[PDB]
Amino acid sequence: SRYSPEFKDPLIDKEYYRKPVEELTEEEKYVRELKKTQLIKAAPAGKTSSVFEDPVISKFTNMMMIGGNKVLARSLMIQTLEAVKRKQFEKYHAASAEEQATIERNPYTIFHQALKNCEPMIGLVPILKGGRFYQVPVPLPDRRRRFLAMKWMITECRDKKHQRTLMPEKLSHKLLEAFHNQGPVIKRKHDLHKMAEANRALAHYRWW
Amino acid sequence: SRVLRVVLLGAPNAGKSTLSNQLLGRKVLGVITEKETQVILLDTPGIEDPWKSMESADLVVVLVDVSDKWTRNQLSPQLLRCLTKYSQIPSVLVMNKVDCLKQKSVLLELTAALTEGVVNGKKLKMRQAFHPQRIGWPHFKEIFMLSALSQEDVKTLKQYLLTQAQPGTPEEICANIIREKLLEHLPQEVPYNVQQKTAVWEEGPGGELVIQQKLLVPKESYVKLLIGPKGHVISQIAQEAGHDLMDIFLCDVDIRLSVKLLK
């Protein structure tokens, strides 16, 4: 690393600095006074104080890049968002009066709910002894299941069975399927939840 | 109202009484009442009483002391006979004293040995790198790994037992507390040779409970061990005992212990 150990990661949150000094508790006030003596790393290219910033979509875009091509990955992400938006507008226009109240048209809400519907709660962690890597059920951390939802969505969309259908079109279709609790990613979550129910012998090993 | 009868079976020093005390919440048949569930713990001696207790068992808790290298690898033949005759009753495995293990991965192998690779009617499918007297029991419904002394994971067993519920004198207390302290502090057979006789049991002028107990022993060496260096041991015992009594009777207790030789 080119940064010395004393350098600290920056805090890009903008409303954080606008809190009145009155609200600040003694601990938060001490933290703020401490921050003045430290060196702060340069903010990396990426996150910004923008109001449209979305860390989940940023992480999904980073997980889609191939070979450092961020422009293409962001282009694909925005194309997918626009495709979801246009599909929802088409479905809203053609719907009758009482079905227009239950049709979501915000693509960010759909993306977040689709990824949430695919998160697994429990997974299997192998453990080594005797030459047998013992598969014990484990409650997945939040970060782990968040990563797994995104990875399953991307791997599902990268399948070679989908011939010449462009990535934004596949991804919007999969996202709208997962929004309604349907599709192969939801089944991949279910086939892990049942296959971890099939191995509840070693369900109490709490020291993975 | 839901009811469960749980029979605890295991080796003599498997900690059955320890788990019963921790699960009851007091160091005491036991009854646990929580909301609409009642659990009746039947603590049996280690291996007629176990069989008679298991006659009325809704669930069986089979203990294995994993720290004991001699018996951790197999169930006792008498125990295996006992489950076989009562195969209809559900059974659960409890691996106790996990804290004493250097290498926790050991329990993995022991599970395969103790459950014969089968639990709750399910199989274990485990590949490897590259590539008669029964020893275990294949009809365990569940497996728990816990330590009785440290209360580690005991709560999980408590909740499991609760969920498994199906449709359906003061002087003695003082003597028991003193005996507990004697057992904890004294070595070898000494605490088993101490006879307790109450000298004074009254209410003092300030409302406290004045207690004077006489500890009678047959040997002078037992007297020396009881008194300890400079009277420390006995004093500690008394002090600790008093504290427990102060909680039991919800009143101030002035407890005085005296040691005398049995003539």
Image (cartoon, coloured by chain):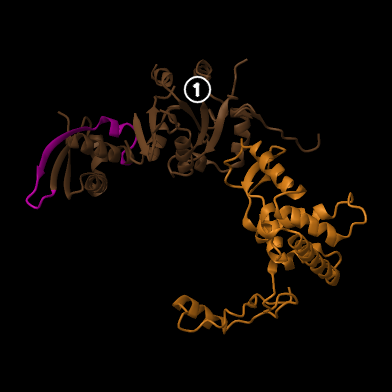
Chain colours: A orange, B brown
Quadrant, the N terminus of chain B: top left
Residue located beneath label 1 in the image: B89
Q: Nearer the viewer, residue B198 or B70?
A: B198
Q: Residues within 10 Å of mark 1 (few under 14, many from 20)?
A: some
Q: Quadrant of the C terminus of chain B?
A: top left
Q: Chain of mark 1?
A: B
Quarter of the rendering containing residue B118: top right
Residue B246 at least partly seen: yes
Q: Nearer the viewer, residue B147 or A194?
A: A194
Percent x, y for residue A155? 81, 54
Label 1: which secondary element: loop
Residue B210 x/y as whole percent: 12, 45
Residue A126 among magenta residues: no
| Residue at image location 25% in from the left, 47% down from the top | B247
> Residue most toward the front?
A97
The outermost residue toward the left is B205
Q: Is residue B92 above or below residue B186?
A: above
Is B37 on the left-hand or right-hand side of A77?
left
The span picked out in magenta is B185-208
What percent of the width, then of the height, locates residue A160? 89, 51
- Residue sitting at 65 percent across and 42 percent down? A136
- Disc 1 marks which amino acid? Ile
Residue B105, quarter of picture: top right
Residue at the far right in the pictured view: A164
B245 with respect to B41 (left or right): left
Q: Is residue B189 magenta?
A: yes
Residue B13 lies in what quarter of the image? Answer: top left
In the image, taking residue A62 as reference, residue B159 lies left or right, namely: left
